[PDB]
Every structure is written in structure tokens, then in C-alpha cells.
Amino acid sequence: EEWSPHVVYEATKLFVSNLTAKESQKFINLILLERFRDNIETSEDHSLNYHIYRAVKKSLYKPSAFFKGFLFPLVETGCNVREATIAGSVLAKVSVPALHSSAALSYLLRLPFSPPTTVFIKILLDKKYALPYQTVDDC
Amino acid sequence: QCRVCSSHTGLIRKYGLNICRQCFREKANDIGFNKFR
Amino acid sequence: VADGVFYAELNEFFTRELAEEGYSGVEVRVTPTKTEVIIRATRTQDVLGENGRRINELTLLVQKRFKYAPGTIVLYAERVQDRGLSAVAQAESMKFKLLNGLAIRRAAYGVVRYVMESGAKGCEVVVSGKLRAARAKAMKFADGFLIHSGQPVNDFIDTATRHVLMRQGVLGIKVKIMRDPAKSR
Amino acid sequence: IIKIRITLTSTKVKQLENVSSNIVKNAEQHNLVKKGPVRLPTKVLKISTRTWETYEMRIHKRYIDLEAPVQIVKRITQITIE
RNA sequence: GGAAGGGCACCACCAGGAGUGGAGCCUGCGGCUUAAUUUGACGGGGAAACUCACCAGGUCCAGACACAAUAAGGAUUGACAGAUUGAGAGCUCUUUCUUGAUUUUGUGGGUGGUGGUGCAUGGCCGUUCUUAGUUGGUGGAGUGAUUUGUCUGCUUAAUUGCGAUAACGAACGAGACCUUAACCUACUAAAUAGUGGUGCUAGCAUUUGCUGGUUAUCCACUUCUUAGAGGGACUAUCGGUUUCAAGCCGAUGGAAGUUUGAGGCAAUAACAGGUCUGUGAUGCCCUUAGACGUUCUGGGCCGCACGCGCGCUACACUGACGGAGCCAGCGAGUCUAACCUUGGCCGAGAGGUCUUGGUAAUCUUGUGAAACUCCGUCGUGCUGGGGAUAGAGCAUUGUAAU
């Protein structure tokens, strides 16, 4: 957690573009998530730098790894609104396959309600993908 | 270099605490250097 | 059973961190390798919050701060009233002070002082019965600001009656405490 | 029988004198041999802040020698945490 | 109203002292010049890289979703080594190959508001009027506007008080609250402080002594170092001055007698004062081939007829040189690093080597600083004052010292 955001960006590119779906799940859930929550939690204005945003952007190339590693325990650890805007712009800018976007929406609709979760569901509804009927029933 | 809130203007660079003289007098009542004389 | 050093350090952390979430006291019990620290609480809707709040916040704050991994210690909560705002605990305390040889005046001053230090808008203690004399007497001890009529009686004031048995006879303690209407919530 | 020196430091005089006097009373009430509370000079840490002004801090130090077994030393060190 | 009168101040004058502006140079501004000499009026703006906000270039990475094509015999995305490649890094295609719609191209409302300036809301670091005389409650008398309070006098640093008197109350002022200074051989108390006595021990004259070594040889103590408790000062007292009132001045006693001196603290009446990387189908130029984001090199920010200014060093004999004596205090010091360094050897020195002590009233440290004291050289001669400028080499920190 003592790296620079350039180092976290490059290591996220390395450890998502090479490691598999479960392995980059463990990488993002252990190394990126705790450094993420400690960059935003320990700061007095509770915002994030630009290169951690680019790291979370580059972590979505394997979408199983992204959703199973980044988004799903973060909302269960307390997600605020700068994380919502930043990781929602992450969730918007990168083209995600429809199945893991559908599993993500099926996750986020079940959560305890929060306007960060509302921003993430709003980004996943900006896709208008070919959703399975279970994801439609969760809506 | 300000490593707290990106506030290089007036760092107090002594002892590496590195708070600007604006925010140093924000956090002046947390360390203990206060008004006696 | 954990030590009072840990308990007082959590008191020091809570008194500076739970400044406007109602930290009344701490109940704590220790089972093998599990220290259960129940935050005794003024109002607990600051503690519970909107859809599960301060308990998760302080749990993750201790895990992030005091270098605890999830699984070693556990954090609990219970819903009670503020000990000063409640007339029941203050009536228990008034009964306690009268049974331990403290007179009407100093016990009434101490209990009303503790209630006004708690943060109640006002309080009143009514003490009736006989104290070393044949003739019965009653004594009012009111402070702050109280209301006596209407639906705000049902809303804002707590009343508690206690029959406290002394060696001469019986005394009737009537504690009436007015809670802060801005903090109604 | 372990000889341990306790070096106490504080910013305010009343709580530091209270802690030192509690050490003296409790180590005196069960017959421990000891040196009295040696009172080090109060060091004055100051910063000249932007005419000019001065910010000050008084730091008070005592130290007390004690000779006691492990149980009494541990109970004294645990209870006197303030 | 350009009447006059007081404060009350060395950012004012007199008594002066040190001076600047005179010489050289350091440094800040202006001007010129440039490709840039980034930009404000000390900007913690000390300084080759960074910081850098400026130039000469070379580059990455953009742009969401929707939507028409394109398909696994291949769109393509990556692990590559070679041809590379200019100054560096990128970039393209030949394979060894993962390829797997993450497609690729061109578009359509805008994702991106890490593109933002304005409207509101809440509010804040430096604050500052750090409110030192005013306010209003009425009274009355006057169509309105106005009189009084808010005054003949006297007095205080003050609208602070006295007094007369259309008068009668209250608030914030102001005094006042906080924090400091100095004297305590009267307390209370010591190996992270010291003093003396005393053991062991070194030298010198010996007739007793002097100088000491000795982080335990023991003791006492705080005389000095130090932590507090208190105490004291409240103008104590005397005499002028003052309605002989609140008060001022001269003198004595006093550690302290100008409010013993300074600064922080409110309430009321001004700050668009400076942002929050704030929220709101907010208004609005584009929505991106812009670099706004990134880099990576090399030059700048220092350049010079000159002007505005502050400093350093001199013009010497109350001085320069050569020796000797060697007097302080505030600080400050290293961890998951290279800090402060004692000592010993080498080197003319710069410095280097080898260690050691100290996370600290302990070691650096007794910081053996400088000015100063004494004795010799000089002999008033731009001199043996000056040290600007320039040459040569040698070392240290820094990747890189032009």
C-alpha cells in the first residue's frame, strides 16, 4: 500500500493483462482494493488521484476478474460517492462483455441501497446489452 | 513537497511534517504549539 | 476477561470518535479468543443508521487502524436508552443513593446534576415520605425546562416511580425527565 | 527481585505529580526500597512563527527507581496507565 | 468651511549613535534582449535534475454508449527476437506464436465533466472593527425633519468618574479574562545536574599543602543546576498636584513602584475578502484528434549601455600579519537508516582511512565560537589596508558541477 499510483497503475496492467480471472480477482481484492480504500479513507477530502482511476480502468479487461475482485466486496465495505463516480466512469469507458455486466447488475440490484450503488446501476443501464432474463427479473 | 493536501505554499519544510502555513494554523490545535506569549 | 486498560482505551477512542452518535457507555465480555465490546447507548439510530452504519464503520475503522484482521475480535451493539435521559436508570440511582445513607438534598443534587450533564432539557425529582420524623413530607427538585400538559407529555417526558424501603418506613421516588426535543429524531 | 527505572514524561504538572505520588504511595505502602522522584528540567520547545511571534511548549520529566518482583511491577505498570 | 487647540510617536523633530545613497561585489524589482530570459507585488521564490509553472524538438493515450457493415478457414489483441533508431525513447512489418469480437472503420444523442466558468444554498484557514463611546427603550416639546439624553463647570490615558441639570433605565464597549517575565542559604528533592568531605591513585615541594585521575568507594546537600508549592506587588509609605473626589507627579522602603512589561480572548457593527478538486434534467463554447493528460531529451528561470533598493567587504597604526591564552548560550542529531560524530593514522590543506559514543541534562559537548587579552613583525607609503577580477592544479556532495 506504499506504492505510487503510477506503480499501482503499471502493476495493475501487468497483473490483469497476464494473470487469470481468479488470480486478478485476488490481486484487485487484496492489493488494489485495500490501497484504494486507504487512499480515499485516510485523506481528508476523501477523493482519489488520476492514476488509480486509470488502474481500475485497466483492471476491467478481464471482466470476471474486475467484477469478482473489485466491485463486489467494496460495496460491502462501505462505498462512497467519489468511488462511485470514478469507478462508474471506469465501468462506462471500457467495453465489457455482456455476461459479467449482467452478473454485476444482478449483484448491485440485490445490495443494501446506496446512491453509489445507484450510480453503478445507472452506468450498467447505460449499456443496454443483451441481458439474460434473470438480470431482467432482478431489475 | 507537500504530501498531505497538495499545499506547497508555505511549508513548515522543517522536520518533514510539511503542512502549509494556512493549514498549519488549521491543525495548530492538534500538536500543541499554542499562544502563551 | 480483558483488562480495563483496553476498555479505557476504547473509551478514549469512542469519546473522540463517537462524539455525535451517542456513546453512553461500554459493556464488554470476553469469551476464549473473542472480546465482545458492546457499545452501550444516547440514541442508537445514529449507531445503526440507514440499512446497516456506525457498527460497520467502526469495525472497519478498528481493522484499518488497530491492525486487526477480520476474525480475531468481534464488535457488537445493543439498543438501550441514555442513562441520564431515562428516568428508570436515574430512579434506580436515586433509590441506590437513598439506601446508602445519602440524604434527599445531596442525592437529588447529584442525580439532577448527572441528568443535566447528560443533555436533558430538564428534569424533576419528587421525594415523598418520612425521614427521621413522625410527620410525612414531600420535596420537589426541578431544574431546566419541563412541560406538563398534552401529547408532548406522551412524546418527550419519561416518568418512573420507585418505592424505596427504609428502616423507618417507605419513600416514593418520582423521577420525571424532559428529553431534548431537537434530538427527538 | 528486578530493579526497574520508570521514566515518566508529561506536558501538564498536576497529572504527572499525581502519577508520581501514586507510585510513591503504592510503593511505600507495601515496603519497597526506592529512590525518590527525580525531577528533570522542563524543556522548552519553541518555534518562531511568522514582526515575529513565538510558540512554546513546556515538557516535564520525572524518573523513579523501583526494586520489585515481576507481579508487582506488571500490576503497577498496568494500573498507572493514564 | 483651507478656524484654532491638545495628544504623542524616534515608520516625527531636537541631544546624539550606527548608517544607506560614495567604491567593488551579493541579492530583489523595472528596462533591454531572446527561442525562453516562466509568472506575481518577499511570494518559505534559496539554488544544474525534480521543484517548473517557460522555450527547441521528439513522442504516447484519447472517443463513452448506441448504431450499419465486418467472424473463430480469421477481426483482432498480447509474449517476443531480429530489420530498427533519430539525440533518446517510441513506431512499422517477417517469423516463434497467444489470437477469440477486448473486434476494426465511419457516424448519431453525450459518456468525460480527472473541460469548466456563472445562479443559488450551506459554510470556512490569515483574519479584523484585534469594536477604548456609542447604541437603542421610551419620555416630553415640535406638521414633517428635529431638541434632550449626547451638559455650564471640573477631572481622568478614555463618554473613567464628580457635579449642575428633561429627565429615567439597559447593553455591548473600555477597563476587565488568559499567558508570561524577576527575588526567594524559609519548603520539597535528586548517579540523564552539581558541590564538598571521604576511600584507591599520579606528579610537585614537603611543615601542614597544590594539581588531579576514580558513571558507584560511600555520605551529606541543592550554596550553585533543576520540578513545583506558595509567597510578593496591592502604586507599601511620605510630600507636591487635583472640585484638594475618582486620579497624576517627585521621593523613600521594596526583587519588582511608567498599568513590573508585553502579547492572545470575546459582543456588536465591514469584508464578493479566498475556495469546496460540493451539490442541484443548473445556463453555455465545444463535446477529443486538443494535449488539459503523459513522457523524454537539451537550453532557460542567472543573459546585460542603464535605472529603483537592501546587504557583505574595505579605504587601515584605537590597524593588518606571526604567534600564544582559550570565554559562552539557544538549539540539533540516525530504524528498519548512513544523522551528529569523539578518538587514532595519512595528506600542505581540501580531505581520506579505521573505528567508537549518543534516539540524547548522558555522546558529539565544557560545542576550548568570534570579537577579546598579551608579545613580537610592520611603519603610513592605494602600504605588509583592501580583495574584486583572472590563471593553474588538487579534493568533496550530487546521475549530470559547462
Image: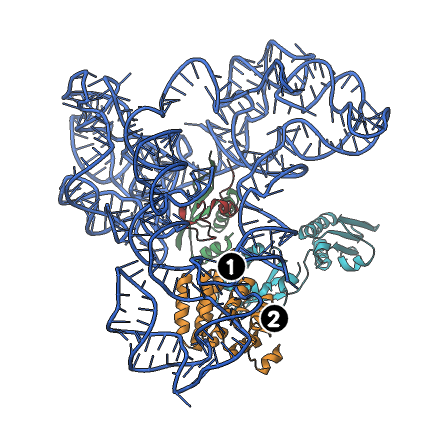
The dot on residue A115 is none
Q: Are marks 2 and 1 on the same chain?
A: yes
Q: Closest to the observer: A24 or D63?
A: A24
Q: Residue at x 53, y 57 (%)?
A: C9
A130 horizontally vs C112: left or right = left
Question: Would you call the spot at circle 1 few (<14 residues within 10 Å), some (14-19), or many (20 or more)?
Answer: some
Q: Position of residue E54 (x, y in %)?
A: 39, 49
Query: Which colour is chain D painted?
Result: green
Name which quarter of the figure residue C150 lies in: bottom right
Name the spot of residue A44 as percent of width and height, x first: 52, 55
Q: Quadrant location of the N terminus of chain D?
A: bottom left
Residue identified by numbered label 1: A47
* Residue shown at 50% from the left, 52% from the top: D80
User: Are the residues tagged 2 and 1 within 8 Å (C-beta)?
Assistant: no
Q: Colour of chain A?
A: orange
Q: Which residue corresponds to the image point at 42% horizontal and 56% vertical from the top-left?
A: D69
Residue B19 percent location from the top left of the image? 46, 48
- The image shows residue E373 at horizontal and vertical percentages of 25, 22
Asked whether E304 or E161 is in front, the reply is: E304
Q: Can residue A133 be seen from the camera position used here?
A: yes
Q: Which chain is cyan?
A: C
Q: In terms of depth relative to the viewer, which is nearer, E153 or C79?
A: E153
- Colour of the chain lettered B: red
